[PDB]
Amino acid sequence: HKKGLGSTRNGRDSQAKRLGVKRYEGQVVRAGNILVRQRGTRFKPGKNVGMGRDFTLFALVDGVVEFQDRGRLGRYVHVRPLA
Amino acid sequence: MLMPRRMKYRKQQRGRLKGATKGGDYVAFGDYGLVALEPAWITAQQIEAARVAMVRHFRRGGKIFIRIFPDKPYTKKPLEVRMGKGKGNVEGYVAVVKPGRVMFEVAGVTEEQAMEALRIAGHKLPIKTKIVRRDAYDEAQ
Amino acid sequence: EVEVVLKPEELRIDVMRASGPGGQGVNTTDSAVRVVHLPTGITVTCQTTRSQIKNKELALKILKARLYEL
Amino acid sequence: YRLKAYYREGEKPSALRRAGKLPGVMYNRHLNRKVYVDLVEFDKVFRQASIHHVIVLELPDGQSLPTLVRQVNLDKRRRRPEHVDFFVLSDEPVEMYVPLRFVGTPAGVRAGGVLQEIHRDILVKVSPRNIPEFIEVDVSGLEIGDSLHASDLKLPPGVELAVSPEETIAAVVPPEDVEKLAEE
Amino acid sequence: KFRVRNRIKRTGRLRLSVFRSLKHIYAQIIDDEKGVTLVSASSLALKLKGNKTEVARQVGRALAEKALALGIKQVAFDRGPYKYHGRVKALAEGAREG
Amino acid sequence: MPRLKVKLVKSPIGYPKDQKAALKALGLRRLQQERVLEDTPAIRGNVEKVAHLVRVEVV
RNA sequence: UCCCCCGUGCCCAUAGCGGCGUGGAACCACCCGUUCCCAUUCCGAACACGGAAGUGAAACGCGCCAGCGCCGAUGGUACUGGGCGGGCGACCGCCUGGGAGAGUAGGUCGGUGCGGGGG
RNA sequence: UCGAUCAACGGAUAAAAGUUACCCCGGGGAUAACAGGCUGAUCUCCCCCGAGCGUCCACAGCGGCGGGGAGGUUUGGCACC
RNA sequence: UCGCCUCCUAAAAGGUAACGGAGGCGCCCAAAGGUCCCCUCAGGCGGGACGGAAAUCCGCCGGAGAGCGCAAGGGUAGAAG
RNA sequence: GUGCGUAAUAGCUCACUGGUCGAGUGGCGCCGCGCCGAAAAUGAUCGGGGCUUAAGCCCAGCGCCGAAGCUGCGGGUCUGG
RNA sequence: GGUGGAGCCUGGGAGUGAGGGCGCGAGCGAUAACGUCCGCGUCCGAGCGCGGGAACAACCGAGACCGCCAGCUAAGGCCCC
Ligand SMILES: [Mg+2]
Ligand SMILES: [Mg+2]
Ligand SMILES: [Mg+2]
Ligand SMILES: [Mg+2]
Ligand SMILES: [Mg+2]
Ligand SMILES: [Mg+2]
Ligand SMILES: [Mg+2]
Ligand SMILES: [Mg+2]
Ligand SMILES: [Mg+2]
Ligand SMILES: [Mg+2]
Ligand SMILES: [Mg+2]
Ligand SMILES: [Mg+2]
Ligand SMILES: [Mg+2]
Ligand SMILES: [Mg+2]
Ligand SMILES: [Mg+2]
Ligand SMILES: [Mg+2]
Ligand SMILES: [Mg+2]
Ligand SMILES: [Mg+2]
Ligand SMILES: [Mg+2]
Ligand SMILES: [Mg+2]
Ligand SMILES: [Mg+2]
Ligand SMILES: [Mg+2]
Ligand SMILES: [Mg+2]
Ligand SMILES: [Mg+2]
Ligand SMILES: [Mg+2]
Ligand SMILES: [Mg+2]
Ligand SMILES: [Mg+2]
Ligand SMILES: [Mg+2]
Ligand SMILES: [Mg+2]
Ligand SMILES: [Mg+2]
Ligand SMILES: [Mg+2]
Ligand SMILES: [Mg+2]
Ligand SMILES: [Mg+2]
Ligand SMILES: [Mg+2]
Ligand SMILES: [Mg+2]
Ligand SMILES: [Mg+2]
Ligand SMILES: [Mg+2]
Ligand SMILES: [Mg+2]
Ligand SMILES: [Mg+2]
Ligand SMILES: [Mg+2]
Ligand SMILES: [Mg+2]
Ligand SMILES: [Mg+2]
Ligand SMILES: [Mg+2]
Ligand SMILES: [Mg+2]
Ligand SMILES: [Mg+2]
Ligand SMILES: [Mg+2]
Ligand SMILES: [Mg+2]
Ligand SMILES: [Mg+2]
Ligand SMILES: [Mg+2]
Ligand SMILES: [Mg+2]
Ligand SMILES: [Mg+2]
């Protein structure tokens, strides 16, 4: 005997987004290289770093990524040139 | 019974039971306590039964402290139903207990009454217990 | 008050083999159930469904009735 | 009271504690050493004593020091201690929860009631030479319901506490009446 | 707190910072990323006329001169709570236009 | 420089890939095979990783 | 070098809150006015201009205090890469590396570049 | 640049519902119904605790709330020959 | 039930299943857009004709608990408001 | 007022003290190994026989046995030199 | 560091797209299933070749070119079979 059952109105979920840091400190990059994918401003653009509409962070020059945590001011991603 | 008035979620994942109580290991209230020796899910109907058992024992007497609280929901599918088609329905609530936890406490009661009391309450619990006194159980600072 | 808690303390529940149609299972499963009330002499049966557990409770859902009337 | 104490070189924590010796450390606002003080006398003493009365600590240096225990971490599963913190002293004024006796009979013990001595070991700020004992309170006036509290007590000259004074020190509440049952 | 800090809008280099005072008006061309002041020109703290605005202009050209001497051609205009008006150092020199 | 002489004594059959590679890195193929290597930190790291399968000798 | 004050930066609460004092010679503020530039969903409060009698009262600066806040060991535990054991299970133990979070002692009412004005 | 609930949303035709106990072929123990098996919630039996019933009097006969097991005859779960 | 978005499951990189847990989208805005210039909330407590227990005033206190068109999350007053 | 006992008393008795005896004592609390709790369906059994200061269990030690694993000797083939 | 049936690039030919047990981490389930879904790892699959485990794909030991009436070991064993 198979006694009938119901179901759930659950079952959904949205595609994975692959957010996060893409280049770490001491890593060489080229102009344009996206360095971080984030939703809010989890990281603030630093020296030679841009930020697109979706808060994406990319290198502005060809240099080596560097990270700086500035307490109450936030965390910064800078791109130090070979200067 | 002995459930929580409100909850952000009605059903919740089962989990696990790694030994050590984390917290609740010393007396801190009454004079004698009942400490859990095996890990387990104590159903509110047991917490209840044990409690009533004590007041019943030393009717018109001391004070009782229930140191645990069933805030975890218990799910159970219907009978004769197959697997799947969603999570079961909540059948009650249980308090998770680990080894070392002082589940109950008593006060303003004779040492005879205290012992006898807790000994009966442990006969209503799905686990093994131990009765204690008070001494280093003074984490006042 | 308005109460009648007939505890399954004086009931005799049986489970004979289904009657009527069915298939390779009407002959095999103890579908049909029969709950008996002894201090009264009332008996209620049920083969409405194809499950003993959905029939002993649905057969009890009646004994509660007739009783509250008698 | 008194008690023997030895110096720990920092070797096999969990072992020195199995062999029978109980681990620990003695510190204060100056120096701080690591030691091992056996369960035998420790236990016996510590229970009679507690963290109210001072103790001696004669090491192989003899150097007997006055102290009160600040921290004693149990073993969770099956009560037992694994560590103890020793606060050395002098004439230096510090704190400590001082024992509490409550001579009396609340009016809450004739028609049902029992005393819940909430904070039965009150913390007070004061120096060594200023270390009392059974700091009693009056209970002869605690009605069944309403009950005493705060620092509204007999603080012998020199008792410069650290309460509120509101910190409910104690209260009297009712019994466990068989009369219950419910639902709905 | 009249916060503002609109000066945080400092992406480039060489900040020409002004300071209006009930009495005087100072100004120094600063270069962060090094945390140093390179050129300075005060109001009556460098001694000057008695007006306020007229004094602004004079202490203006003053700085710019001393500036160019060091090769300080272009900069960016500051004074946080500034409110760009009156005491406007609309000075010649300086390749910060404005 | 003081060298190491590790000997594969316990079979790697049943242990993780990495542990089987460490052995490769060291140069151990068969059971009972011995190999004298330099004592550098990079050579120990792997011998530490496979301690349970190797008998080491400082020579 | 060393002091005091004014601009700025870095550290990003050991910088704070709240008490208690100090400072007007210079700086600075508040002040004096609203002709003028410029201003108010209404206000010269705020912005802005011209000033210069008075005050350091408000604000701000500098000191001292730990009540609140913030910081925070040393020990010992939790947990755990890897290796290994006991049970019948839920689970429990050892070895070898790592090692908190609470809590205790205790710390703190700041540190510091650069440029100006005053001894 | 416009016309898609081509929403079964990588979208078969521009255009499409049922029935078979009158049935048929190719396959599957990749998958149901019997029986077995693993499981033992359900089921049956027995035990721990001692509120309370038994005029008195916890077990002569009973046992509130709760706790631990056995068996593998029931109803199921699983889908292993 | 079928496509898309948010959280969890997810084992501190990314990713990760089940008829697992729980909600949203199939729009909207010529100002809700660009830029320049100003301004800073929610609450709590007092004081105020109509006046709730928040209408609008005043005053201390209030580092963000408000707000950000709509779900959730991340972010945010040194502004995205 | 401990238990028995009464319809409530009575009656027996004890915590308790004298007491000849003239010595080890009652307690509680951990630990190692056992006892009970313990009933299923064709003939039983730890694999069998058979084991008890063990042929069981815990803790030390040395020696042997034991694979197609590793050596020794011979041979083949494939790669690199 | 690391010369390994390592890697990287281009191209010819593929099979596979029913997995399974076990350990650890979760969900689902009843902290049921030789259950079911993922994750890390392993082994069987293809090592039903070998020794141990009474017998037994995946547990312990161990990766079988062939030959030997030679030797040392592994797990497991050393009262008799
Ligand atoms: Mg605590
Ligand atoms: Mg039919
Ligand atoms: Mg059937
Ligand atoms: Mg501004
Ligand atoms: Mg193996
Ligand atoms: Mg102002
Ligand atoms: Mg672990
Ligand atoms: Mg630590
Ligand atoms: Mg810490
Ligand atoms: Mg088409
Ligand atoms: Mg599709
Ligand atoms: Mg068609
Ligand atoms: Mg017909
Ligand atoms: Mg025909
Ligand atoms: Mg016909
Ligand atoms: Mg036909
Ligand atoms: Mg056919
Ligand atoms: Mg076939
Ligand atoms: Mg099958
Ligand atoms: Mg079947
Ligand atoms: Mg068969
Ligand atoms: Mg019951
Ligand atoms: Mg059967
Ligand atoms: Mg079945
Ligand atoms: Mg399957
Ligand atoms: Mg992740
Ligand atoms: Mg992860
Ligand atoms: Mg924009
Ligand atoms: Mg605009
Ligand atoms: Mg308000
Ligand atoms: Mg036993
Ligand atoms: Mg041998
Ligand atoms: Mg050869
Ligand atoms: Mg060869
Ligand atoms: Mg290959
Ligand atoms: Mg190819
Ligand atoms: Mg392919
Ligand atoms: Mg598949
Ligand atoms: Mg696989
Ligand atoms: Mg697998
Ligand atoms: Mg399973
Ligand atoms: Mg399976
Ligand atoms: Mg196959
Ligand atoms: Mg293989
Ligand atoms: Mg076979
Ligand atoms: Mg075998
Ligand atoms: Mg085998
Ligand atoms: Mg081989
Ligand atoms: Mg070989
Ligand atoms: Mg044998
Ligand atoms: Mg051996």
Image: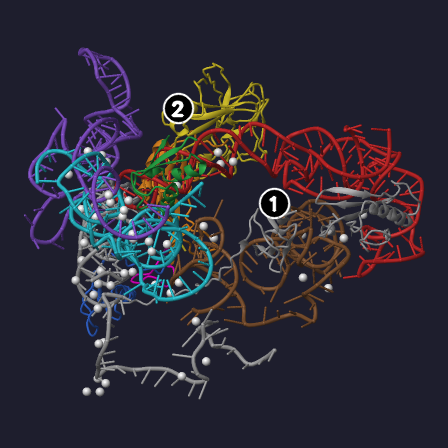
Chain colours: B orange, C blue, D yellow, F green, G red, I brown, J purple, K cyan
The disc numbered 2 marks a residue on which chain?
A: D
Residue B48's tag is none
User: How far across and how far down the image is residue B4, in percent?
Assistant: 45, 51
Residue A46 placed where, x, y %? 64, 50
Front residue of this view, candidates K70 and E29: K70
Q: Are marks 2 and 1 in contact (CB under 8 Å)?
A: no
For label 1, the residue is A69
Viewer-nearest residue: F54 or G41: F54
Q: Where is residue A19 in the image (x, y as percent from the top left)?
A: 53, 56
Q: Does the magenta stretch include residue B103?
A: no
Inspect the magenta stretch and tell me whether residue B82 lies in it. Answer: yes
Judged by its main secondary structure, the magenta piece is: loop
The answer to whether one can see residue A4 in this image is yes
User: Magenta span covers which residues?
Assistant: B75-88
- The answer to whether the residue bearing label 2 lies less than 8 angstroms from the nearest atom of ligand 8 is no
Q: Mark 2 points at which residue?
A: D21
Image quadrant holding the N terminus of chain C, namely bottom left
Number of labels in the image equals 2
Q: Which amino acid does label 2 sit on?
A: Lys
For label 2, count other residues whose C-alpha is less than 10 Å away and answer few (under 14), some (14-19) or many (20+). Answer: many
Tell me the distance, in whole angstroms, between the alpha carbons under discs 2 and 1: 46 Å
For the C terminus of chain C, the quadrant is: bottom left
* Residue E31: image location, x then y, percent: 75, 45
Q: In which quarter of the image is residue G12?
A: top right
- Chain of the residue where label 1 is placed in the rendered structure: A
> Who's the residue at 84% across and 54% down the image?
E85
Q: Considering the numbered disc 1 on the image, is that residue within a helix, a strand or a loop?
A: strand
Amino acid at dot 1: Asp
2 vs 1, front mark: 1
